[PDB]
Image 1 (cartoon, rainbow, N blue to C red):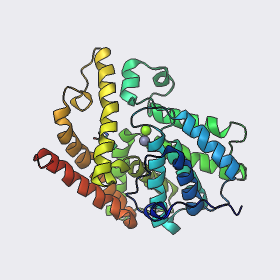
Image 2 (cartoon, protein in one colour):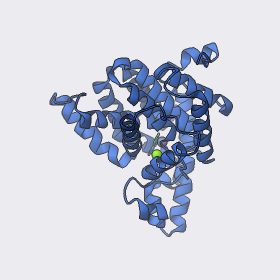
Image 3 (spheres, rainbow, N blue to C red):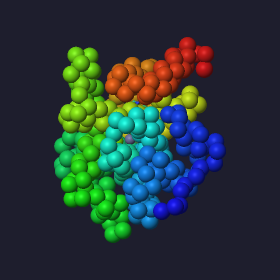
Length: 313
Ligand SMILES: O=c1[nH]c2ccccc2c2nccn12
Ligand SMILES: [Mg+2]
Ligand SMILES: [Zn+2]
């Protein structure tokens, strides 16, 4: 009960910032995550022995893929920690608990392929889940690990709190399906602007939690330029592998996923920042003003990609 986690001074300070990079030392990531739970949630939320066993089973069920890996899980959990810490009183005990676990679990057992490639391949997961295929699988994997013996970190909750937290986590994980982002942000935009947004309306809270999940999941675009640029290589390493597997099925991949069209990467980043990232953080900042630093950093990185095309780097 009296066992705190402490980070070194640089990490203790930089971890509160949105643009924090968790570093190349895999063995520190579990401790970084426990640190964030204790400060975000309390040292009482979870039984440390159960939490540590949950975390190491989650780590084990992420694959060695270039991007959709254990490092991404923890990066996304840190972005959610930063949002929750900058919006202290807006979220319930249950929500703070649920959302950090949802982030850690959001991409469990990812293979580095889009929902589209699973459909074109005719993967068994595509027969069992027709939409948000991987996302329904990630939530399924989460429930499996929670049911391993000694792994039920939620065991002190009541029957009803337990169903609530697993509903928060299910919705949170489904919302990381980017195909659902576009309609969700558009509805939030309308509700903010026509002034009907209501945080006490649970259908509204769900949408706002969904946008936070998209914001955390894309948070590679909100880092300092050198982190953003190097993470983009891992992202495109998966896109090009999927493109290779599309060509093997007898289908030209879209140019973003074709490794013969690397030249077109900078313009593909522009489209993605304008079409997805900037609108995501704009709406998020309108609803939760203390998340403005994510919008500022995203803008800085858009400007950095424009410089890449003007040959300035
Ligand atoms: O160019 C990019 N950059 C990204 C950066 C972070 C997360 C998703 C993406 C992405 N999805 C499609 C294209 N994309
Ligand atoms: Mg995902
Ligand atoms: Zn993700």
